[PDB]
Length: 158
Length: 158
Image 1 (cartoon, rainbow over the protein chains, first blue to last red):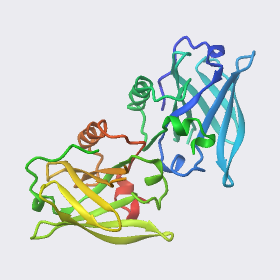
Image 2 (spheres, chains in turn cyan, green; image 1 turned 90 degrees about the vertical axis):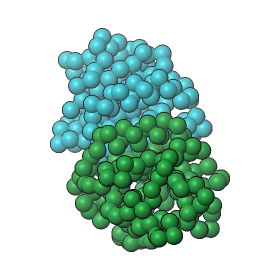
Image 3 (tube, rainbow over the protein chains, first blue to last red; image 1 turned 30 degrees about the vertical axis):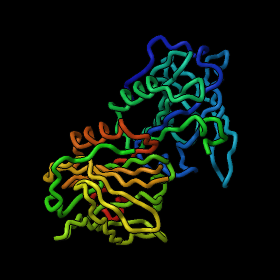
């Protein structure tokens, strides 16, 4: 279970452009295939005035790169959002400095977990990846992926 | 380029049973799919009297788990073997204690690299994984997988 949250998170300040630099998951099958369920690439975070968090995503499905929009609804805890879908899915914000990196996890209630290291630019931020790997020491992850700057500038990181 | 080799390697002492606990590679496509080219599971190392290193492997191909035998031929350096195939492929032994763990990499001469953490038993050896992650700090890896003890006891780690 993810216990790591961002104290004093200001959700309006995570708005805008992000790159999915690194991804990790509890199960190999969540990230292995181009089309695996957690292989989702962030384009934009769009907080609402009410304080919900909209994700603009890309996903490989039916041999191509589709736009997806997910709304994660606010809870009583600022760093935790709930995705209305068939299953009880939580989004947790682990850590961010707003200007360079943001760490988040998706988790279900069976237990499945997928986390990402987001960065503001198409660059390999070794300090952000250090914070990401420190966070995942606490988590039972079995696959980890990372992308180069060329991939980061392509649709679905091809 | 892998510069890390086992000083004073005794190849006859790596004989016998091994488990592919963890795998990492330079390119996501080498390890992502059940059938990806570097997704090969070690069963046995069989040194020859002449000092060549035979690998007994499992590989997922055509929706099933096949036996494969590879011979890596000795070179003038004890920790480096050459696989006779269409391409110039090297096997490097990075580190081993013979009794618990062995770290090795396959590399080509384009550059592609795939490494594994082998262990003698179907257990998660955190100290072996620490040595594996230390070795990979020197290498440009973009995917990392690890297996649980249940998977380690199944054909092709299903």
